[PDB]
Length: 126
Ligand SMILES: O=C(O)CCc1ccccc1
Image 1 (cartoon, rainbow, N blue to C red):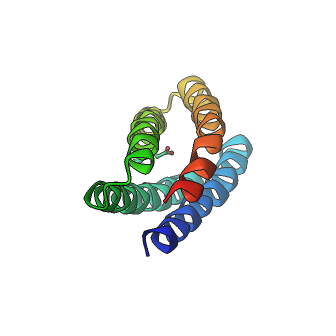
Image 2: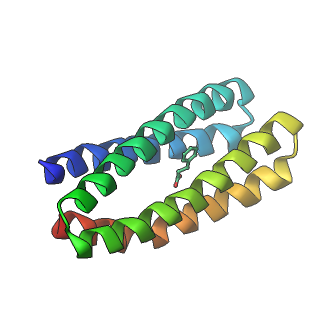
């Protein structure tokens, strides 16, 4: 069901949260080799999450579930805000700019925290 597809998407999102916090610890400790690997792992988790969200939104549209489509249009827009901040973070790492990396990391944390009440609303709406 689309609802169980959203639970699968939610779990992939939680996996990225877990890997992100582990990446943050490694960054603070200066373990750049670990950070590089965690960033690759996160890039894969976001690409997976983004595609699953796209399938869920498309399915909601085909089902005519207007409220779920509204919420998923907002949530996918916000996901892209997080994604853009991720890609800038990756570039900051490549460039050795730890000041920008710290900035983009905190912003990504606050954008994600903000998007959580909506994430829970979608589960109920599908
Ligand atoms: O953290 C997010 O909100 C998603 C970030 C993301 C999404 C898709 C590709 C790269 C990063």
